[PDB]
Amino acid sequence: QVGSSKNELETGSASNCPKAILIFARGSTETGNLGTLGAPLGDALESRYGASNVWVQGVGGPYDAALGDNALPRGSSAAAIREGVRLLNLANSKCPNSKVVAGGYSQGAALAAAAISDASTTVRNQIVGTVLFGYTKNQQNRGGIPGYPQDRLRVYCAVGDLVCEGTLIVLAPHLSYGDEARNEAPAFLISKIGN
Ligand code: NA
Ligand code: NA
Image (cartoon, rainbow, N blue to C red; front, top):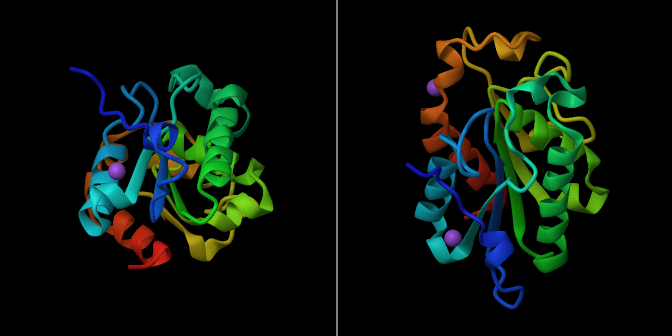
């Protein structure tokens, strides 16, 4: 087995920008750059618009999804958060007229939150919608992304997912977001991108 990965923002032509670009950060120990939730989420967007009209991009490079990095400031390493910021800035520099949507699972939700907070006011305006699954900073950020408007966010925190409740206790409900990745989350992102 090889982890599910997509790198379409990095490989795409700047002369052929898509309607939408998804940047997604996986959860700790997951393989590839999309993990378990990123691939179904990108597939749902590509089913809606067509695969040529969405660029799906996972967060990799120095983001190694390491278990220890959940204990760091903001819930991931500074280098992993910087990698999110590099991809958001790449989306903006290559394809400024494309709609960006962001997502993350678990540590990846913390990475996504921090990288969106760190991005410019113009980049945040380009990110029309964000979905967080099992958000490890839900309690500490009071259900939001600092500096990002609530209408553009959905947080999926399962009943009994204690990572949403200021701990790092990972129980069965933390593994229950496959349906939101397939259904509610792409439906929400689609509403913000437009038809
Ligand atoms: Na695509
Ligand atoms: Na679910």
